Amino acid sequence: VLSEGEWQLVLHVWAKVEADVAGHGQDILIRLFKSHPETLEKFDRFKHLKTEAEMKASEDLKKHGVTVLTALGAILKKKGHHEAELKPLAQSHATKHKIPIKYLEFISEAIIHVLHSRHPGDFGADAQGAMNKALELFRKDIAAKYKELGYQ
Ligand code: HEM
């Protein structure tokens, strides 16, 4: 569990992210696609994108980035009590999209890298550790749902 102090660090930097959801959302998906090309293959919707320039130019990609961050934002603001928000997400990603747990770890690294790049002053080592724990909590709860459904 994260302490109240750790949650405050997480939410403080997340408030900054909400000032430019589209920009943050776009950078995170591009980071993920570049570092782990296999993740792009899960998206029939973005499979055609080959270069980073093509990726930055896609409005549909930017739109999806907003969907991912707003859904994650809703979860983080729940400070651990995210049962109702997480269940639906685990179900679709396990049974419909077929997203292995490892890919969730990849996008977690992408989120941390982007937060560090856009907010050096508010994303120090202490905030970085708090965010990592929050994302680990996110992955832990999702993995439990996957196991229940038979997806590891
Ligand atoms: C921070 C973690 C993530 C969050 C919050 C998230 C959230 C969402 C949401 C809200 C949707 C739309 C509704 C739904 O189907 O549930 C969605 C769709 C989808 N997600 Fe994720 N996702 C995450 C990570 C990933 C990862 C790591 C992958 C793939 C490697 C992925 C692949 C997909 C795909 C393929 C769709 C369907 C896209 C379409 O055809 O419109 N997601 N995700």
Image (cartoon, rainbow, N blue to C red):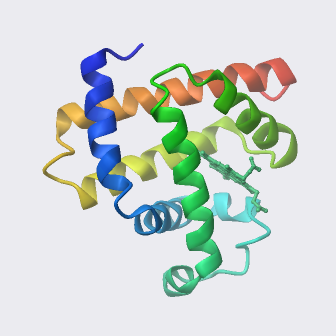
Give the vertical position of 132 relative to 53 (above or below): above
Q: How many marks?
A: 0
Q: Which x, y percent locates residue 38?
A: 66, 59
* Foreground residue among 102 and 131: 131
Q: Residue at x 65, y 22 (%)?
A: 83
Residue 20 lies in what quarter of the image? bottom left
Q: Which x, y percent locates residue 116?
A: 26, 52
Residue 55 lies in what quarter of the image? bottom right
Residue 61 lies in what quarter of the image? bottom right
Residue situated furthest left in the rendering: 121
Quadrant of the drawing holding the C terminus: top right
Quadrant of the drawing holding the N terminus: top left
Give the vertical position of 102 relative to 142 (above or below): below
Q: Is residue 86 left or right of residue 11?
A: right
Q: Is residue 103 left or right of residue 137?
A: right
Q: Residue at x 53, y 43 (%)?
A: 72
Q: Residue at x 55, y 61 (%)?
A: 66
Q: Which x, y percent locates residue 37?
A: 61, 64
Q: Residue at x 44, y 61 (%)?
A: 21
